Amino acid sequence: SRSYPCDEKKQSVIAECSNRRLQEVPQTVGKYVTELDLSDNFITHITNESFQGLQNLTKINLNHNPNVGLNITDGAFLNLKNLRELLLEDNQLPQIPSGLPESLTELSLIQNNIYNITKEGISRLINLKNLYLAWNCYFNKVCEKTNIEDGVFETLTNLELLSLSFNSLSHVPPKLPSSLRKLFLSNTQIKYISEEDFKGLINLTLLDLSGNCPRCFNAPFPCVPCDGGASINIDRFAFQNLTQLRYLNLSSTSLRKINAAWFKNMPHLKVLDLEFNYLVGEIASGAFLTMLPRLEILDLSFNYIKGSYPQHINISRNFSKLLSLRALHLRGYVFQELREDDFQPLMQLPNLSTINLGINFIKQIDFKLFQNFSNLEIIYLSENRISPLFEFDPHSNFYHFTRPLIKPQCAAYGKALDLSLNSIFFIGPNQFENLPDIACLNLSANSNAQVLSGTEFSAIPHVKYLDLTNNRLDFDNASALTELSDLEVLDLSYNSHYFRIAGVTHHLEFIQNFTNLKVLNLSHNNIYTLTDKYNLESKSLVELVFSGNRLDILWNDDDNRYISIFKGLKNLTRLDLSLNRLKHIPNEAFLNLPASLTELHINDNMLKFFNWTLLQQFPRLELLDLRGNKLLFLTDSLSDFTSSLRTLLLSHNRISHLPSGFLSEVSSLKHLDLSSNLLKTINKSALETKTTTKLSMLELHGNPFECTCDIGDFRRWMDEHLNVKIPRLVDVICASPGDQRGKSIVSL
Amino acid sequence: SRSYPCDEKKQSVIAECSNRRLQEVPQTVGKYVTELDLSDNFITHITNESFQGLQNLTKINLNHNPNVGLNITDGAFLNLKNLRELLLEDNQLPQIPSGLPESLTELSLIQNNIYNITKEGISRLINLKNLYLAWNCYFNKVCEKTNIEDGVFETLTNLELLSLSFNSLSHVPPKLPSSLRKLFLSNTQIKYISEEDFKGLINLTLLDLSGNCPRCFNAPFPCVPCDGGASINIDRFAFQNLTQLRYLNLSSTSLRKINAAWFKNMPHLKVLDLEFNYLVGEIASGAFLTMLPRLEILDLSFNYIKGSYPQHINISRNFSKLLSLRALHLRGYVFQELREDDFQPLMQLPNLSTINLGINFIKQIDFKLFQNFSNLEIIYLSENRISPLFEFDPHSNFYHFTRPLIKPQCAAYGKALDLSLNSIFFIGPNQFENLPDIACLNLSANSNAQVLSGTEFSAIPHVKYLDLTNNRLDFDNASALTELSDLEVLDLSYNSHYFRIAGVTHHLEFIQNFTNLKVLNLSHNNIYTLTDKYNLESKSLVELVFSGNRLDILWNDDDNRYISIFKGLKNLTRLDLSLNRLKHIPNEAFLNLPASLTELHINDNMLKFFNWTLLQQFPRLELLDLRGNKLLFLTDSLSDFTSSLRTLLLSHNRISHLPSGFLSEVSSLKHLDLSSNLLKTINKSALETKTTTKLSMLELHGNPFECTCDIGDFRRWMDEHLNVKIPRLVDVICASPGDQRGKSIVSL
Ligand SMILES: *[C@@H]1O[C@H](CO)[C@@H](O[C@@H]2O[C@H](CO)[C@@H](O[C@@H]3O[C@H](CO)[C@@H](O)[C@H](O[C@H]4O[C@H](CO)[C@@H](O)[C@H](O)[C@@H]4O)[C@@H]3O)[C@H](O)[C@H]2NC(C)=O)[C@H](O)[C@H]1NC(C)=O
Ligand SMILES: *[C@@H]1O[C@H](CO)[C@@H](O[C@@H]2O[C@H](CO)[C@@H](O[C@@H]3O[C@H](CO)[C@@H](O)[C@H](O[C@H]4O[C@H](CO)[C@@H](O)[C@H](O)[C@@H]4O)[C@@H]3O)[C@H](O)[C@H]2NC(C)=O)[C@H](O)[C@H]1NC(C)=O
Ligand SMILES: *[C@@H]1O[C@H](CO)[C@@H](O[C@@H]2O[C@H](CO)[C@@H](O[C@@H]3O[C@H](CO)[C@@H](O)[C@H](O)[C@@H]3O)[C@H](O)[C@H]2NC(C)=O)[C@H](O)[C@H]1NC(C)=O
Ligand SMILES: *[C@@H]1O[C@H](CO)[C@@H](O[C@@H]2O[C@H](CO)[C@@H](O[C@@H]3O[C@H](CO)[C@@H](O)[C@H](O)[C@@H]3O)[C@H](O)[C@H]2NC(C)=O)[C@H](O)[C@H]1NC(C)=O
Ligand SMILES: *[C@@H]1O[C@H](CO)[C@@H](O[C@@H]2O[C@H](CO)[C@@H](O)[C@H](O)[C@H]2NC(C)=O)[C@H](O)[C@H]1NC(C)=O
Ligand SMILES: *[C@@H]1O[C@H](CO)[C@@H](O[C@@H]2O[C@H](CO)[C@@H](O)[C@H](O)[C@H]2NC(C)=O)[C@H](O)[C@H]1NC(C)=O
Ligand SMILES: CCCCc1nc2c(N)nc3ccccc3c2n1Cc1cccc(CN)c1
Ligand SMILES: CCCCc1nc2c(N)nc3ccccc3c2n1Cc1cccc(CN)c1
Ligand SMILES: *[C@@H]1O[C@H](CO)[C@@H](O)[C@H](O)[C@H]1NC(C)=O
Ligand SMILES: *[C@@H]1O[C@H](CO)[C@@H](O)[C@H](O)[C@H]1NC(C)=O
Ligand SMILES: *[C@@H]1O[C@H](CO)[C@@H](O)[C@H](O)[C@H]1NC(C)=O
Ligand SMILES: *[C@@H]1O[C@H](CO)[C@@H](O)[C@H](O)[C@H]1NC(C)=O
Ligand SMILES: *[C@@H]1O[C@H](CO)[C@@H](O)[C@H](O)[C@H]1NC(C)=O
Ligand SMILES: *[C@@H]1O[C@H](CO)[C@@H](O)[C@H](O)[C@H]1NC(C)=O
């Protein structure tokens, strides 16, 4: 029996049951299921019958039910002897639910309406390791100060993580377990940290005190400062017994001075976050810096003085004692010029690999200074003024984004310089003098309108990944970029400015000159006319992204000039012609696509016709993507035209008929996506081969199926081929007749 | 009887029958219909039965049938004694159809496959005034040279317009009617114009000879030059008897010299088009210019010398004899600098109002020179390099676009300067010195990232319409633009660059300072956080476009800061909150919308809920647009909440139920759009008032209607309210049951 309404899975056994409009815990869950995800449904009541006979349940996720309060009876879960993880986020719960099972090691009640943390609801959960209560009372929510029963956490002697962020606390609760490794108290309205607060927490590796006495100017959320925008008050001995602290978060605590004695018994401190404070003075002096010879990451972002646009950044000499430092983040300090001598203190630190000066309104940099660091790998200068020479995710970081500064594919080639979002509108015979051996260069969004001519990158000739996106480049010279012999990836996306104008000349001939070029992105360039040379040619190129151009124009029926546009891409395996307004492709142009292709995307066009017989000329073709078109016709003889194709994507088309022996004899086809077409039925001979079907996935959701006895053949087929996954059966719905309408074809 | 499948109309009586998937000329056309539009259907055969009993037909449009050859029997139309205009474009016709009715005054056979123009098909059509045969053989189409039977047009003595463009002709046909006013022979492969060719065409006001011996370098279409890219050869006396010529089109005829004697007997010539020739030398000397004292429009665009980037443009002194000149178009000449003395010859011409220098790669202009013209009104400098100081529509112009240079709403305020698509990335204490009294200023797409501060426009303080779109403006000063006291329209669209960054400050306070500001466009700015002042305020503002911002964030449930964001817009009547990702609007924020509103758009959001009762606080509200959301619920008591609302737009929502007495008692509602929702039926009490319904339009197409006997009530209602137009009944389709599926609810 193919499972329903949940999708079950492989490896422990998962019931994927989220987001399928369920009203109750459905009663047809596989009795062998260990993990049940019921999140994002319309479930409103939970009782002792809800999970009965699912006694092997280890994890239940009920996050985000119902979608626009969850009712949980006392003891509702108390049966499930093996229940370890219970996730009850975003449920509008008024209280901790009563009579939870003592087997719990993980309980998340994030984003509910619980202002009372009691012994009654918690103190018995003696096996709890992770307890999450964040984001119950915050910002301008109408909510109550949170009452924590004295001693409530004391009995929890296995507790390693406790999160109370984004609740109104006022004080650090007394009588916390000495088992704690991670304590989260961000934005809890605590103004004073005493000596007793953390005294017995000798296993703590992480303490987050961010957002208490916040710096409120220009906050993107409702923000309540401490009287007079004063600092957090942290007793001299607050951290004296926290010898195992690796992580300390003091962002937006309105700090003006950092007491070096806070760090005296913290020899392992690794990551220190001091964002959104007032530490310009502390950065320029910085006694505390001497206490941190093992620090790896230091974040001093958004410490700018309101109203101030100083000429220079002022870094203490004491930064030279940060011997382990690997990353320094100095965004939002705000300054006009970076000179060589201003970073002297950083230049001997052996492991300093990332310098982040994002968002400083810097107008000029003496670039030669970067060489003098011992080993930079990521010089991040995005979003400055350099010129020619849930509202908030409770499970994310609130003060910044955690994404890599540089795209990992670009940074993997070596040393990276990101000058994106500046004003280098023209390079510059000497723009890149005195730089290291830059491998990854990001010049996206610099308003560049120059004609590149083959000499502009001559001082950084080993760039291997070049990002030129979102400029205004005038591609009017056949030698552009040819100085970059090692170039492997080139991204020219969103440079439509001159391609748009038919009366200026356009030259893409340089593409052929590269011997190592693997990936070229020409997307969203509105390319519809080229000058003299009408063809793209390269012996190396493996991937071309040609989405968001005008192949409808290039391949217009009355024009032969571009019918070989891609044929000289002799090595190509992956081609993307999406978003090109194509109504049909001339036969001859389709036949002139590279025979090497393994992957072809023509999705989101307006294709009314596809010549399937032309697939014969593409013996390596494995994936064909035709989603989002206006196709009506499937061939009845695919096996005559291909023995390679593994995946065929056809969702969002107008196919109302699957032909007799459609499947036959297409051995290679593993995945067929027919979702969102106009199929009313599927007849017995449509899926039939007497040969061996390797079909493992068939998508059918969003078809207007007629649920009369004519569906019974397909139903029988589903019974007889349990190995062919049909996902989201709850969305494989009857459109007709009216008694059936809305119901899954399976439940009939 | 409500008509079907066509929509009939008012004023002569129109059958709008286009684009509704018809297979035959439908037989249910109103016998009183004078004009029948059957274009864009799937019609494949036309016979003598097709229009029978539609004897009052004056005009038939069969353009673009079938959609992917039309068959017309001999004499098929010969009945229709009153047929004057027959439109048979884009039909893939192999021949002129035989036995057309001699009543024809207008025949269009554009874009067919007709290579033979015969007496047999044409010579009897003695009343023809306009005959269109263009675009039958062209570019790389597989087609034949066109054979014109000698004398074929001679018998057509009422012919005033003849179009043979985009066919292969080789020679001007002999024996053309002397009745001609307009002769179109563009791109006909004629290389020589003799003395006999136009000798007897003394009524001609227009001659188009463009595209014969074309200039082919960088053409955006297949283009065949005359041997050696030679010029068109026009005999000295070719135009000697064309005294009534007003329009002459010689674009792309590869002209290097213009013979002044061509214009000797052309005293009324008004518009002369000399685009895409090689007239740089002729522009600098230009004897022919002396022959043209009545010329109003002169177009010399794209006469650039390939490969050449001269410093200056060189205009003959002879331009000073163009006494009537009103517009001069000099795009694509290509030059580096415009100096005062270079336009001396233009400065005394009293009526010269438009100068177009688009697309010249101009780097600098001495702006003071514009003042010295007698009266410029449109100084068009778009798309240069100024710095801080159907494939082709057969019914359009092929060599340029015909749109206004400047938007008519901007140009209507007075003198216009369009500096769009340049590199004025910073203004400039002296940027606008020595200009006339500029009323309409276009600075769109100049990569501007400055902080405007209230002094930048002080030398052009009477700008009334200001276009700042598609820049990178840093709105970080409360005085920005306040020097512009007369400003009425301000467009700040697509300046999301700094609004996107939460950690920089953002200031929109200046808005309040203007006393005449009527229209403000803040669209696509990703606005989600502002500094200090959270409200937009203006006592004058009548229209705010706030589409493509983040009201979902601004109005987040946990934040009160922005719940009055628009309430200080005390005069507002039109507000656009589309494309703001709204899932719902807090009640209090909706109630704080200006009570003056007459027009409110919240389309293309994700609204799952709408509080209809809040409409009580908006007594002037006439149009509510909620299309493109996820609404399920309509109130049953609209009349309790509004007596003003005239138009309610709800297409593309999820409404499956119309309530009992929905219509009641909403006197004011004229137009209700319920297309593309989930209605299965409409019950009798849903549309029922015993009061007076002023409903004149009801849209229902794209609803999954169940066509059983439960539809009969609505059908009866349709019969009983013929005055309530339901458009596109062919698209008001049955989804169920399967016998009915696909069929219009009306035809059941
Ligand atoms: C103050 O600084 C501290 C120390 O840096 C910082 O601690 C980090 O908090 C976040 C919680 O926001 C933790 O990140 C989570 O870690 C867990 C456990 O490994 C993961 O499950 C989470 O990943 C899931 O969720 C993500 C976001 O939705 C998804 O993108 C992801 O793909 C997963 O689904 C998430 O990474 C992080 O571990 C701690 N750091 C530790 C313990 O070292 C804290 O957030 C800062 N405080 C504030 C208020 O900013
Ligand atoms: C050479 O120059 C000549 C002289 O300027 C130029 O003549 C113009 O040709 C066009 C045909 O392209 C005519 O424009 C049409 O005029 C008719 C009649 O009034 C209108 O019906 C047309 O408007 C409809 O079609 C438009 C385009 O689809 C729609 O936008 C519009 O809204 C209407 O539906 C259209 O305006 C124009 O009248 C003549 N000029 C005259 C007679 O003065 C000629 O095209 C140039 N040749 C080439 C090849 O470029
Ligand atoms: C221009 O096109 C290039 C090449 O297609 C785009 O880069 C590619 O982006 C895709 C994702 O869109 C990357 O693949 C993904 O990466 C991770 C694995 O690392 C995986 O999770 C995903 O399932 C998927 O494989 C791909 O690596 C990346 N390629 C390179 C060379 O960087 C680029 O994004 C396009 N540019 C723009 C502006 O759209
Ligand atoms: C920013 O918003 C302004 C104001 O809404 C936009 O300008 C307006 O554009 C509309 C059309 O989108 C114009 O109305 C139309 O004009 C003609 C009549 O002249 C009519 O045919 C149409 O039915 C409709 O009325 C409106 O006049 C124009 N307003 C002004 C003051 O110019 C502007 O386009 C927006 N900018 C961007 C970049 O989107
Ligand atoms: C080059 O710089 C641009 C701009 O910072 C980067 O674009 C960002 O890319 C990430 C993910 O690729 C997106 O989620 C952000 O939206 C982008 N921001 C903008 C403004 O586009 C780009 O990724 C950087 N490229 C490389 C190779 O590191
Ligand atoms: C200001 O300049 C811009 C760029 O030339 C104009 O934007 C064009 O507007 C027309 C119609 O409004 C569009 O059909 C074109 O697509 C636009 N081009 C681009 C690149 O956006 C704008 O209309 C001009 N504004 C005024 C008021 O004249
Ligand atoms: C109307 C433009 C004619 C041909 C042309 N295209 C370009 C272009 N894309 N960018 C330019 C940037 C600066 C100057 C000219 C162009 C340009 N031109 C004219 C041109 C002049 C000299 C040399 C070249 C080289 N292709 C082209
Ligand atoms: C991290 C930025 C802090 C506040 C700020 N926002 C801006 C901004 N939007 N544009 C600038 C352009 C140039 C220099 C600074 C800013 C800027 N800043 C810092 C700032 C410094 C001095 C004065 C001001 C005036 N609002 C703001
Ligand atoms: C710098 O990094 C390397 C590991 O990559 C490590 O071996 C060395 O100990 C580091 N130096 C310091 C002072 O932390
Ligand atoms: C073709 O692409 C493959 C895969 O990257 C690469 O190894 C090979 O070097 C390329 N061939 C040529 C001729 O460049
Ligand atoms: C498909 O292309 C082949 C070219 O190999 C041709 O024989 C056949 O005519 C094409 N089918 C259609 C419908 O154009
Ligand atoms: C300039 O234009 C006006 C009409 O606006 C007209 O009266 C006058 O005759 C024109 N002058 C010439 C020389 O054509
Ligand atoms: C309000 O708008 C109307 C319509 O433009 C205008 O006449 C009036 O002057 C404006 N009112 C104020 C106070 O500016
Ligand atoms: C609609 O808004 C009014 C506020 O006047 C309120 O009484 C009613 O509760 C609102 N309805 C909903 C469903 O929020």
Image (cartoon, coloured by chain):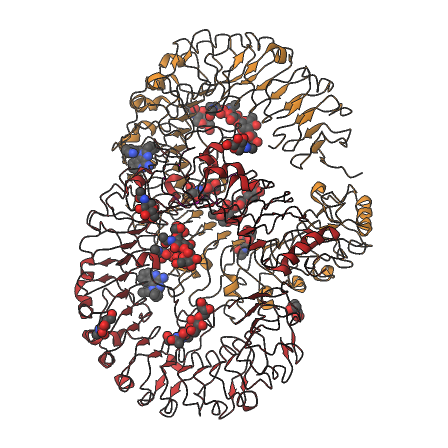
Chain colours: A red, B orange
Magenta extent: A563-585
Q: Residue at x 56, y 55 (%)?
A: A697
Q: Is residue B376 above or below residue A39?
A: above
Q: Residue at x 20, y 56 (%)?
A: A435
| Residue A14 quadrant | bottom right
Magenta stretch holds residue A78: no
Rendering coords of residue B650 (x, y %): 65, 53
Rendering coords of residue B130 (x, y %): 59, 19
User: Residue A531 versus residue B440: which sits nearer the camera?
Assistant: A531
Q: Which quadrant would the C terminus of chain A be assigned to in this image? A: bottom right
Whether residue A229 is visible: yes
Q: Is residue B251 above or below residue B712?
A: above
Q: Is residue B54 above or below residue B244?
A: below
| Residue A699 quadrant | bottom right
User: Residue A613 versus residue B330: which sits nearer the camera?
Assistant: A613
Q: How many marks?
A: 0
